[PDB]
Image (spheres, coloured by chain):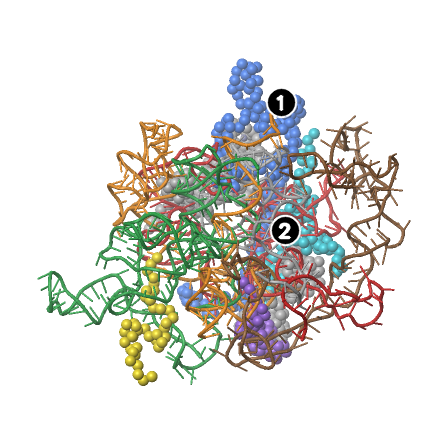
Chain colours: A cyan, C yellow, D purple, E blue, G brown, I red, J orange, K green
Amino acid sequence: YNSFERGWKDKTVHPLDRRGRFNLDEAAAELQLDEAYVASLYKPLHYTYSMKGQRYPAEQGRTSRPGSLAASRDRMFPLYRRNYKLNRELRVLDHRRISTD
Amino acid sequence: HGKPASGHKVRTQHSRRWWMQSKAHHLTAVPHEEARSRPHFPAYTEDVDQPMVVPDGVCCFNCDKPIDGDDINSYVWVPSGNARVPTTQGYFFHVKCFKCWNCKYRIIHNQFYSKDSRAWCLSCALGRDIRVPTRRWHTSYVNTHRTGSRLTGQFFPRHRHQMEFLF
Amino acid sequence: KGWTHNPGHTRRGGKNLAWRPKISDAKLSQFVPLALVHP
Amino acid sequence: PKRKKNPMQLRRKTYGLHFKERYLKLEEWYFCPLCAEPKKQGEWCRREDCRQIKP
Amino acid sequence: RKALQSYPVPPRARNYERRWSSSRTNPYNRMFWRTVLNEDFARPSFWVSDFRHKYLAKHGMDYQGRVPASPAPGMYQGFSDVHKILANHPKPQRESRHLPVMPMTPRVVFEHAQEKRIDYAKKMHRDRRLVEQLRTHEFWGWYMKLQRVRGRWCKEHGVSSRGVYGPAVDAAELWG
Amino acid sequence: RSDNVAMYFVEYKNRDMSDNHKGEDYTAGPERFFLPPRIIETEKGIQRPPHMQMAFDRWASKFKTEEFHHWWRLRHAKLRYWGVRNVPHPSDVDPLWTEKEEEEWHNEMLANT
RNA sequence: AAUCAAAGUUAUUAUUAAAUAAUAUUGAUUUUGGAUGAAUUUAAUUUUUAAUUAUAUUUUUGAAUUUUAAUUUUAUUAUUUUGAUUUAAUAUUUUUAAAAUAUUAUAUAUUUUAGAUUUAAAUUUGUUGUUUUAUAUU
RNA sequence: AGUUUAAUGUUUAAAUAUUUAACUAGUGAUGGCACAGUUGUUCUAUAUGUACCUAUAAAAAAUAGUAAAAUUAUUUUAAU
RNA sequence: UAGAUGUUUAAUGUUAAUUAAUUUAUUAUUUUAAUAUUUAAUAUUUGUUUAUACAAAAGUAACUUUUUUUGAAUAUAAAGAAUUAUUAUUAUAAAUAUUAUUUUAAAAAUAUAAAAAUAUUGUUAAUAAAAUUAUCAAGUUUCAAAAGCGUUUAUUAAAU
RNA sequence: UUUAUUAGUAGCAUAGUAAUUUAUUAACUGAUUAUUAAAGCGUUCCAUAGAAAAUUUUAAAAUUAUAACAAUCUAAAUAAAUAAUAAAUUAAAAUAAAAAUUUUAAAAAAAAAAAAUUAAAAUAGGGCAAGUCCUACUCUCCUUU
RNA sequence: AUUGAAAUAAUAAAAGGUUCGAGCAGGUUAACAAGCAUUAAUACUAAAUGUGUUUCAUCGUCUACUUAUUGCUAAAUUAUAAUUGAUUGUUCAUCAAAAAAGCAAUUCGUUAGUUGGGUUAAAAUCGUUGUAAAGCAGAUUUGUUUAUAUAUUUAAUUUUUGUAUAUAGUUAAAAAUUAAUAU
Ligand SMILES: [Zn+2]
Ligand SMILES: [Zn+2]
Ligand SMILES: [Zn+2]
């Protein structure tokens, strides 16, 4: 807090973890791990897979207000849109794998 | 004649006959009455005498495929105290090769029976026949990389180890 | 139910030494003038 | 409180030198020659001139 | 309270009772020693323990051999929820010779839905340390660039980085 | 403003004899908190020790992404769930650092060019 | 130090309520069944959605009571087409929200200080203000 | 590591929570649906059957003058 | 002064035949219901720093455009204690993320106890079943009275 | 007066701290002997283990002695609730009272901690009155199987 | 008017007492525990913490324990606590105590009364009250008024002589170890 007046600001955001700037997809290419998947490891699993999760209400985005257009939860938080290909491919059992007749 | 003669079993964990029945008889020296009592085992077995590392000529007991050296916890490394015979250290199994070989389901409660270099389920390896469990069939509940086996075996003073107080 | 830290009957209020001197009335009464003449 | 207080009870509150000294005192101030803003003594700005030589 | 017959598999931990007993965990390792040690404990699981009563009658002997597991195709065909009149084995088959196929009861499918969500979990962990062993692995590799560029700069600018004194206080190898 | 705690400005003594903070200005904080501090124009011709100013932007590099611009957008939702007065909605919190603010700095590393 | 008695006006917006009236009434707030029905069934001799002009009788002595009123004759279960009539009621919200007199070592508001004191209601079974209720505004 | 005690809490973070003692081995059981109010259930304590079992919900004008609380309008014109 | 010897309202107050000053005099010391005070210069509140699992009930204050499958259809974030509260909802699975809400210059009590010589129950109805500890957290013994080990709303020679 | 076996001052109607013995410096403890126990008694009695007592003994909880703040729990600035509230300018203080505990009456004086008083309390504790409740049995009475 | 009994954790609406400005029956006969005239005073004891009295020659009132927590004695420490009065919401709950039981006891029973083990005991302090305080001070104090007062767990001196079968009396040292001023 180098503020002189604390607030929702001048709260030094990470007074640790100085090894910033991780190029995930670039690093994910070295590991050969489906770039869309690796980036999902580093955000709460609520945000990517079809899991029970708790969302903040401002995060949900408001209806079209007189002051502001309808701000959908996606167009303000693109990298939080769940990827249901990546869910299904990983988490759910496909009809295929148990098709017996 | 203090009256309430039937009671709660109020003592019991406040006895000296207890303090001797709470100990663990592990593979250490720790003569007795000095091993840990409530959790039954000391955390962080120090092993400076012998480094206790995973070997290079390591392989799955059940499957026999070579095992990743140490970069991973895909292998269930059961060091049965000092083993030597199964490998330089104890038996080794990838997490998915940890099933009973004969009946092919999981090793219930994880007690297995090394039948001629292929881990057999104790019940089948014992002759019994009830051959399907309820919870998870083909994968045991085991921990990985000895993390479930470090409740027992070879705590720090594994021997006389009097080099300490001698000159 | 005994042994007070504060032994004695030193009263609370009567301490002025001019209108209530700490002198036993046995030894103080001998000054009460019962033949008082000038006033 | 086993009684409500008439104003003359609430008004005695405003006589002790505790109410007065806490609320009803004007602060002594002056114009910071560098910032031209009112200022108390012993306090300065976050600014080089105000910080090297105390205005 | 969510009758156990609703859960796909009966629950792992089974809470009981006992006002005067406070411990979450069911005491396994006791339910295990009995059962492994005593054959009788668990009902015979009819077939593997039938097939006697059908050898004794047709052969005049005790079977005196290990009974085959995996009940023969055609046995327990009217039963519907066998699971007890068996071991937890599947309903054996039709009376056919087609290759064995698991009759995909709601239970078998759930187990498939575990062994995919087990491979899912062990895969989300296996490659956290794989990228964690780049971040810290490459942070060090970069940090040593820092101590090198600091190492180079601290020679031309001569900042010995060892106090206000000259090296003559170092050469003594005392504190001073 | 959040409580009557006093605020002192503890600064190290002479910096004109320093090597890292030679002629910096502290009359005001950095604009975005990952931006290096304003310099006294009379000594604008100062360069720094590289190990100090090459590890800084290593740290300041994580806020120049968009994943932090999502953690910035997001945080403004927390402070509203926790209701903190005067917090703009995460819909009008356009990023701190941006591509227009990219072009200057990569061309401000002309030293390594 | 101590007191000093003290502010009655928002400003601005328009078709409910209640009884009454003796004409309708198969169950108010989506589109049965959607195989073809068997799954969308409420009915029976009792003060009942049926509501009866007397004081004498008679009666477990003491809570029990009067019989067609004119035989299809009108005391009968009720609204749109006078903001449906009439009489009683009248608001509810939006934002309004204010004010200058009594000492100077102390009993309680009157200017001239002194005099002055149950706060009431009940309860007082004159155990005679007997231990109860009341913050205030409307 | 959730439960026979004790401290704190006492309109408390709780119309039962924090810390803690005790206890803890249930192939015989928090649990498929099943029993309902003059009655179910009860390893029985007049205990519980939706946060006081005096069940809730509903419908009454029960009784309360037989020491409960009240009972609305100054300036009067015959006593006990 | 002013009828008289003390307890049953005075009303053409717009001529309820009204029409520019009716100056409305009539208002229940408690009851509920609505406001407003006192307690209150307050009790609570205070956000400075970071050790990962995935089900179903439960909600639906709910934004939308976003690339589900190769199934037709169908639907995927949010509870309960009155709350954004004590509060891992443990159906599962996994094991190195530098995931990120806690004001502040004092002594009384008090919640509480690090530290520390003697003494060991003289305190008290009665010490000894009474948090954690790397100094690794455990009293021993005798006698008398006392069954089963399950089970209980004031928790036991209760009832099994 | 079943009272024989058996234990018996015992969860044993009083009598009591039972009388003896120990034990303790001090024995309303507890254990022992016996033994007519107000009216234990054969389902008695013994045996008895973690319980509750009594000793002996040892012992860290800050047990008396004994007092001994290291820790965390500001003020101020901000938000603004609760019990209670007839009033107070009297409230003190002393004394008499008269029905009462005293509170009055009278005389005569003269900000923050603590809980002595005001109602610091909640709510338990009584007993009486009328009302209703609920349970019980040779004597009251139906619906009764 | 058509039987007799219960505490049922009895209750609901009321007032009114067990513990008192006055009464009653069983302690050496007689002075004393204390079943009826008030009234949210809401149990005895302990802990802590006070107090006004009154009581012979200075002058006077600090004992700690054991058993039981009943209360008050017994009795051990050489020698052993004056008597009244007002006192305990601050602290405990041991007792007394509300179907959890049980024993003997009374009951036809429901149950009743001795005894033992069980059994929440509690709110932000507004007024008075009092302890402190109000940041002040070159200075204790005229008079108000005083939480503050040298001893009651006994030695060794020294005079053991005076007096008579044993023997006094001022004091001192030590011990109980602590100092106290609002304009
Ligand atoms: Zn393997
Ligand atoms: Zn097997
Ligand atoms: Zn300035």
Mark 1 Cβ inside 8 Å of ligand 2? no
Same subunit, labels 1 and 2: the answer reads no
Crowdedness near tag 1: few (<14), some (14–19) or many (≥20) residues, C-alpha within 10 Å: some
Which residue is the extreme one toward the bottom?
A: C38
Residue bearing mark 2: A43
Task: Name which residue lies at 66% across and 22% down.
Answer: E95
Q: Residue D42 placed where, x, y %?
A: 55, 76
Q: Which chain letter matches label 1?
A: E
D54 relative to F33, above or below = below
Task: Name which residue lies at 37% across and 45% down.
Answer: B161
Q: Is residue F85 left or right of residue J62?
A: right
Which quarter of the figure has residue G120? bottom right
Amino acid type, mark 1: Met
Can I make out residue A38 in this image? no
Q: Residue J58 placed where, x, y %?
A: 32, 49
Can I make out residue E169 in this image? yes
B77 relative to K159, above or below = above
Residue bearing mark 1: E75
Q: Quadrant of the C terminus of chain E?
A: bottom left
Crowdedness near tag 2: few (<14), some (14–19) or many (≥20) residues, C-alpha within 10 Å: few
Q: Is residue E52 left or right of residue K160?
A: right
Q: Which chain letter matches label 2?
A: A
Q: Quadrant of ligand 3?
A: bottom right
Q: Residue B107 placed where, x, y %?
A: 53, 34
Secondary-structure class at tag 2: loop
Q: Residue A25 placed where, x, y %?
A: 66, 51
Q: CA distance from mark 1 to mark 2?
A: 52 Å
Task: Name which residue lies at 64% across and 48% down.
Answer: A53
Mark 2 Cβ inside 8 Å of ligand 1? no
Q: Quadrant of the N terminus of chain E?
A: top right
Amino acid type, mark 2: Lys
